[PDB]
């Protein structure tokens, strides 16, 4: 079997590492991002609260990226075509990746979408956030994990 079968997300403890390819073909490994805050967002193109908040994230991203915060938007296993088209129409600049198999979703215990996790520079999960957030709200979270 695999040890990751029994990996577990705990508030105030190290995030379950994962490895995905983003839509620009680039490798993301969560552990590689130690030194940065990470806003880990689980989403979908059909989820209206996800759709409405993602422009907000997009307007916040340049601001917080320089400050060493990464946004990783994990899509809930839709097609490459459905997702590339969504990202395209919105002009998203932050990393987007499809969680093939919904594996990472399972590891993270995600049900309702959208769900976000705040991961700080140590790679510790500090907060789990459920439901659509406002731009003001999102910026708050992003400040909370600025390195």
Image: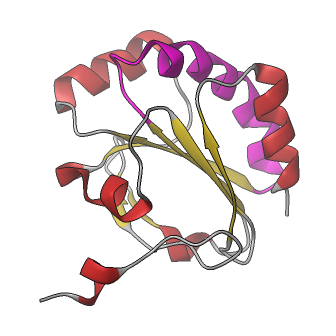
Residue, far left: 1
**Magenta span has 51?**
yes
Total residue callouts: 0
Establish if 35 lies above or below 41.
below
Q: For residue 46, what is the image quadrant? A: top left
Q: Which of 102 and 84 is in front in this view?
A: 102
Q: In this view, does 119 lie to the left or right of 142?
A: left
Q: Magenta segment range?
A: 43-68
Residue 131: x percent and y percent? 58, 29
Residue 35: x percent and y percent? 73, 73
Main secondary structure along the magenta-highlighted residues: helix
- Residue at point 56%, 37% (across, down): 94
Q: Which of 12 and 101 is in front in this view?
A: 12
Q: Which of 41 and 128 is in front in this view?
A: 128
- Residue at point 43%, 60% (across, down): 108
Q: For residue 33, what is the image quadrant? A: bottom right
Establish if 20 lies above or below 56.
below
Q: Is residue 147 left or right of residue 3?
A: right
**Magenta span has 32?**
no
- Residue at point 31%, 49% (across, down): 25
Q: In which quarter of the image is the N terminus?
A: bottom left
Residue 53: x percent and y percent? 61, 20
Q: Is residue 73 left or right of residue 58?
A: left
Residue 80: x percent and y percent? 19, 32
Q: In which quarter of the image is the C terminus?
A: bottom right
Establish if 87 lies above or below 104.
above
Q: What is the image's colouring? A: secondary structure
């Amino acid at each position: 079997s695999n040890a990751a079968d029994k990996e577990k997300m705990q508030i105030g403890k190290e995030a379950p590492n994962f490895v995905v390819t983003d839509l620009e073909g680039k490798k993301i490994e969560l552990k590689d991002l130690k030194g940065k805050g990470v806003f880990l967002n689980f989403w979908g193109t059909w989820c209206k609260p996800c759709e409405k908040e993602m422009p907000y994230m997009n307007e916040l991203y340049p601001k917080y990226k320089e400050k060493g915060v990464e946004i990783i938007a994990l899509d809930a296993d839709e097609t490459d075509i459905a997702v590339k088209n969504f990202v395209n129409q919105y002009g998203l600049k932050f990393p987007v990746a499809i969680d093939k198999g919904q594996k990472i979703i399972g590891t993270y215990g995600v049900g309702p979408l959208p769900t976000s996790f705040l991961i700080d520079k140590d790679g510790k999960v500090v907060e789990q956030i459920i439901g659509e957030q406002t731009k003001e709200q999102l910026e708050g979270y992003l400040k909370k994990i600025t390195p």
